[PDB]
Image (cartoon, rainbow over the protein chains, first blue to last red):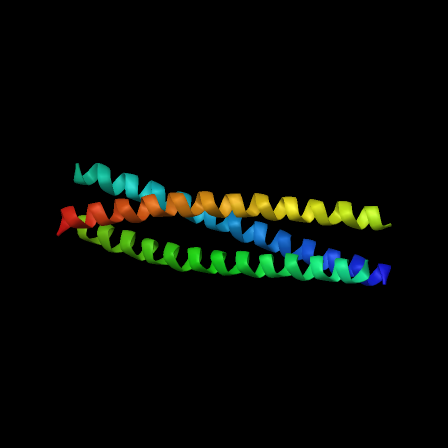
Length: 45
Length: 45
Length: 45
């Protein structure tokens, strides 16, 4: 039972890391879009 | 105690799934904004 | 062992809350970019 719990915890932590990676990927792309909007606005103004 | 731990684990996994859903929703909207920026830039150029 | 598991669970839940905060931050910024795109498109049209 202890080993089952330990395995379950490792699984959850692995999923958490996957989620963290996805968040990092979204942040990077979101930063590119912010930059793109700034450039387009500067042209429009 | 085993049952309490099992319940706690299910709760955590449920929250993880909720988080995964939110990430998926953000990715979809972010994709729309990327497309919108591409169309606006093409008009500006 | 029970205490180790309890500590591990608290750690995981704390990370989950951190993730939730980051998601909330991304959503807010994404909302600003959606608004910016709407304003730029209205000028272009």
